[PDB]
Length: 149
Length: 149
Ligand SMILES: C=CCN(Cc1ccccc1C(=O)N[C@@H](CCC)c1ccc(OC)cc1)Cc1ccc2c(c1C(=O)O)OCO2
Ligand SMILES: C=CCN(Cc1ccccc1C(=O)N[C@@H](CCC)c1ccc(OC)cc1)Cc1ccc2c(c1C(=O)O)OCO2
Image (cartoon, rainbow over all chains, first blue to last red; front, side):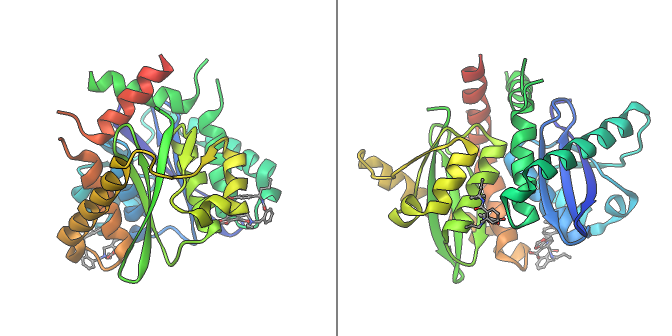
């Protein structure tokens, strides 16, 4: 549970926003890329796993599950690469709702920056700090610290 | 102290590696940019503060301390922007040593990727996971979890 993350790819402004969600907390990291490719997804997972103890990643689609470059990055970084089949049907709903909430936040900040990437990092900040009471950033630290002890 | 980070800029391959160090743990995040500017440093701090609870940042030089774009990002993200004067002289030394260790790790991995940015994220991963017994990634989670509770 503490080490499981889900990839999610959504689109805005003709660009792709790649998101990693820590499933147990709802904490996210995200980036804007011009298109989803294996190399961009592999680089994103390398960043993520140097920053949090990523044990398992559920990939977002079959092309990133198949990609040799993504499998190579997961080898390099010690991540178990898994498919992202929603065996629990509640799961695609949770992801869908997250994409809608993120796009809502992006719209609320959009005029505060020229570049979409800046708006997306403002939305990551607001999402991770929102108290639901604990925020997702607090939840992820508590879960992982509890795992370490 | 759980919320204090130090900026650090080092150079390699004619490019700039911008590093944020969580001072109490030694955990780092880093990126490669073509040159240090206010806009790049501001964007880097916006990413960092969406991911960890960044209360104070000691800037790496006077140009980033003066920059109104950097001050604006620190406003946006709730960070107190401070100078980085090494009132404790041991601080100079610790940062210098870290830059030498990072460059050493980058050389150990450099042939495993074409682009310097990939080598620098491999180095961030090795640095944060190295046990010296706890790693810096474990220390930062413990410190922040202790602070939440
Ligand atoms: C002079 C800087 C260039 N722009 C100017 C701008 C252009 C259009 C609209 C608003 C603004 C504006 O000044 N907004 C303020 C917030 C106002 C409430 C703001 C300040 C610092 C900040 O730092 C992260 C983010 C936002 C901001 C910017 C900075 C760094 C970046 C960017 C961008 C970008 O515009 O996307 O892209 C990647 O690195
Ligand atoms: C076909 C992919 C392009 N290259 C090929 C390459 C070129 C030169 C030398 C080695 C290799 C090589 O295959 N290395 C393996 C490890 C071998 C032990 C590797 C695999 C996945 C990985 O994912 C993060 C990192 C490394 C890797 C790469 C991927 C994604 C990126 C990159 C780069 C880059 O080369 O910098 O830049 C930004 O996004």
